[PDB]
Image 1 (cartoon, rainbow, N blue to C red):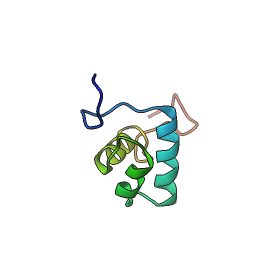
Image 2: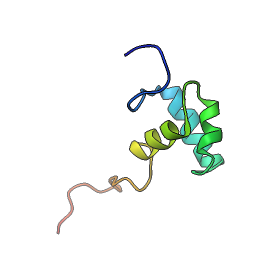
Image 3: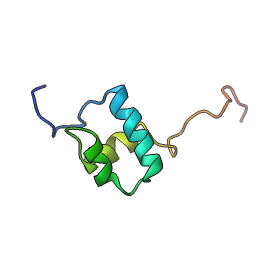
Image 4: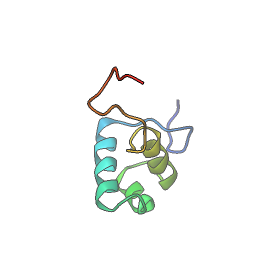
Length: 70
């Protein structure tokens, strides 16, 4: 919408995601605060949200299998 950092689920660019996804994998899903520093206009809340939002394993993703019986 307008210039700033805070907001409702701030947008995200491939780059930001690349750095985040990695950092989280290196430092882990605990140093969310430190990771935020890496990205400009980002905070633990965003890093944690954006992550669990789309970037997360728990998410119900397909496992090399589509149409399965039962």
